[PDB]
Image (cartoon, rainbow, N blue to C red; front, side, top):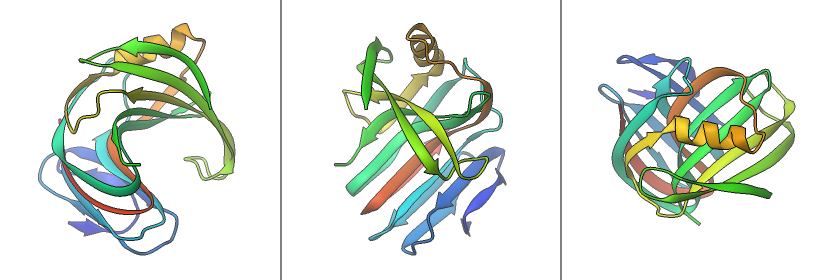
Amino acid sequence: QTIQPGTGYNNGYFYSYWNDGHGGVTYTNGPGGQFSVNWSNSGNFVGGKGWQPGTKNKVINFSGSYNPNGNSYLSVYGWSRNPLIEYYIVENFGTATKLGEVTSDGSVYDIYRTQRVNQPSIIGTATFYQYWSVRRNHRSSGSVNTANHFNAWAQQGLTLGTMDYQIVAVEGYFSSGSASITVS
């Protein structure tokens, strides 16, 4: 069903849907691991379905339709605690510091680390690091072996702590678009 921001469990899956208070986002939970989102001149928002907690060895399957107009991400998305890390495995997008590369699931990824200062997080406003794996061959369906990325991040010294949630998420940032995604 169409819901307001928050977290919970739906049809066997953990979901998280967050936005910055701007209207113009419609997030809908569907059957199984399905979710859909429409956004028109939104602010910043994140929503998707997955697992609570995640694991460092999950192979995540996804397929769907992804049509952004502006800044947007379709990625595997999740959080760590001790250390507090917000991580991204970007499979597709709309319109730092490079630490290395990794070849996985039919494409090369570029490894980046960024820092967010005094920003919303799962523990509230905080300062934390972000890890990025960004696919060069964009796609909207396939499977991601998270262990390939986590071990690649660890090689470059990027540590992950206690795995929090782990979802396939659509992110928008002052843009418009539509997406419908099935996770398994």
